[PDB]
Amino acid sequence: MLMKVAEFERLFRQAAGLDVDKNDLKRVSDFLRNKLYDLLAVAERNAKYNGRDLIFEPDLPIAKGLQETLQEFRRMDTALELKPVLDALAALPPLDLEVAEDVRNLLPELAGALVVAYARVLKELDPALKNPQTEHHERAERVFNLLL
Amino acid sequence: MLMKVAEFERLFRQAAGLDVDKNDLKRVSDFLRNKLYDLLAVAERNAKYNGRDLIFEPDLPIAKGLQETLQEFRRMDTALELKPVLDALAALPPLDLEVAEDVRNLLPELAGALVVAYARVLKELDPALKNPQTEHHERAERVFNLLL
Ligand SMILES: [Ca+2]
Ligand SMILES: [Ca+2]
Image (cartoon, rainbow over all chains, first blue to last red; front, side, top):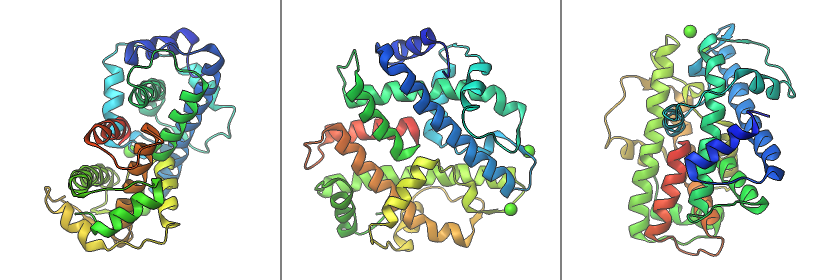
């Protein structure tokens, strides 16, 4: 998955005080992994459009709000490994272009930001929520699908 | 505002089957106007990053999900005028760079996609909602703020 199980749990807990059922974490990981993949697919397209042989941070379609959530994640002093993210993404078609070092280190942080955003979306959908189950996740995904 | 009152009303109905009044539209329009402005502000940064003095479509940080929503909007046969969008954006500080022709024509569509996404978020917050109250806008905005 994108990160260790305990890592997912730690983000859900600290960011929104939520406890995610293990039977849902795999899907959460694949869902956010797919969103991260989409950020990179758009980034590769932008890199080629600008005549570059490498993908850089500006190539990723990260809007101001997501950027601020990313900073929100960074303030959590939570270091996530790169390997699990790259391995998760490798299940999908490989990018043609090399990603710049700025982006490589960014990927795990983005994974964290995505989980943080996802957890908070769940909280907006159900303010008193504590233990989301399948149905909460399906709904959270529908919301995410609208903007990311 | 970003569009005619009639067009806002139409998008809210076609997108989420929601009704909207005056109090709603002024707040909604300004919020989405600011979101659209932010896309452009980031686009300007991206244009400059790529050594251009003109903003093109790839510069806009449009993630795949938002792009799908734009395509969803385009399927609603609701053509929006460019001028109301530019007038709305004029209330904010002008960018240094001019936008290219393809971006100009895209702006109204983005305004429409944003309304479509906003209405659908409101609907997710409460599938039984018919007319969004201040409570709902506050939550819908918080959801958008996490991603845009
Ligand atoms: Ca070019
Ligand atoms: Ca560069």
